[PDB]
Length: 268
Length: 257
Ligand SMILES: Nc1ncnc2c1ncn2[C@@H]1O[C@H](CSCC[C@H](N)C(=O)O)[C@@H](O)[C@H]1O
Ligand SMILES: Nc1ncnc2c1ncn2[C@@H]1O[C@H](CSCC[C@H](N)C(=O)O)[C@@H](O)[C@H]1O
Ligand SMILES: O=C1Cc2ccc(Cl)cc2N1
Ligand SMILES: O=C1Cc2ccc(Cl)cc2N1
Image (cartoon, rainbow over all chains, first blue to last red; front, side):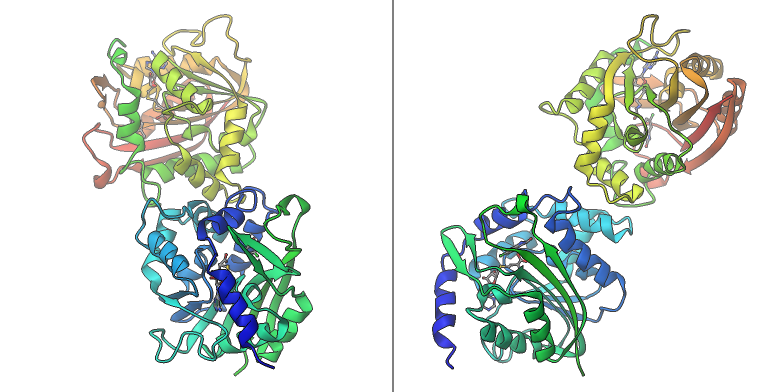
């Protein structure tokens, strides 16, 4: 009926979100181990690489929805878009990205991820070049709130509508329930042009994860709930695959059961 | 040969394996070309067996990155103790070891098997069983009671022979010597400088015999090899740095017969 309470709880909880702990929890080993091809990191990168490798997802502008403190989700993307917008709710995350953009030593090191992306893209690109291009193509880092009908605000800086959207582990991680999730998907969809593409990666059947002091409440979603929401938002689903989280990667940082990858094209 | 007593490993790694010659990003540089020759050759599946020996390793490992997944027993060698020490520092992940990761990465990249560079380094470190003294000017370069399994199924040698031979004849004889280490029907991957007469290694100034591709080809023949492949990389101007007067690099894939 009324979305304010749940959304308020969410915003409250994220005030405690610690980027460094979150990076360590999910992007340092064992989950950040890119050597095991059956690991989640390599699967995520592979979903992205293969999708962009079709040549079917291109344009001038791309918006990454809920970037947090991570850039891996753009490694394969960056060679297909001149203009990239990164976004996040939390200033601290936006500053994390700032540190990487300035190429500071105190910044999180993504070079393994950059290398791995070069590896599976199979074009013999060195990772320093991939990183240099991503840094050059990120044109802005913006506040965002997906619960707003205009997630970027009014008169945003972003080129709208975008040719493509990327969003990894955001919607389910900030929506108290499925209806909120659906509305969030509707909101970000207004930023995408008709015939444009959305690459959505997320947690399956997760109810909580840790980011330092912050223990965050997640709406657990299934593949089928994800498919239906995409259709409900005006997408044709081109691809929807599932990674089942291996027991050895269940580290107590969350109760994630799996990860989904969706390639969807906005009808129009 | 006394000149090699002033040879500084770090200065050599600096001159040849750090930028610009060590930049692997540009596909037209010497580093990537070398790795490609090695990778492509092994990818054929025709160079294989159980044991491999690297002749004149110096302080470098890149020349075995593609090799290591085809040979369970690897022997590295050099004339200088300091080079063997520098190798030991990398093989044992000791302090102040040279950083080869860029090369491991590129080998993984070129090979295209989706392998992470750490697994690659791990395997190489696991398969190098020993680092031995050696002198190619000796009829038995490894000495008599060598811990090395002989004959080897395959040899690798990069920038050693021409770099240690006053003249063509010495070069030919040294090739003769190392060839005795190789099992008949075995393979030799030989990489070397073309038309070079000197190079620097810190305080060391080394004399080199300037050799041509045809001269390299004829040497292998005269040593009893069938030349399966012989390619030339011409050294671009921007990689002419003042550390030597190398004109090009040759890669030769030869088979003892
Ligand atoms: N109301 C809201 N609207 C849009 N993004 C939000 C939000 N509340 C929290 N977020 C951001 O959602 C992110 C979830 S973490 C995922 C980060 C990154 N995309 C990855 O792939 O690892 C956090 O960065 C959080 O700050
Ligand atoms: N008389 C001799 N017999 C065998 N090796 C020798 C030698 N005199 C010097 N060497 C070794 O020959 C090497 C030349 S440079 C090292 C080349 C290295 N494998 C790479 O590819 O870059 C030096 O390590 C040097 O110590
Ligand atoms: O591999 C992934 C990365 C990631 C981010 C956030 C959450 Cl809740 C779960 C996972 N698992
Ligand atoms: O690229 C290469 C590597 C190398 C080793 C030794 C010498 Cl004398 C010259 C070169 N040039």
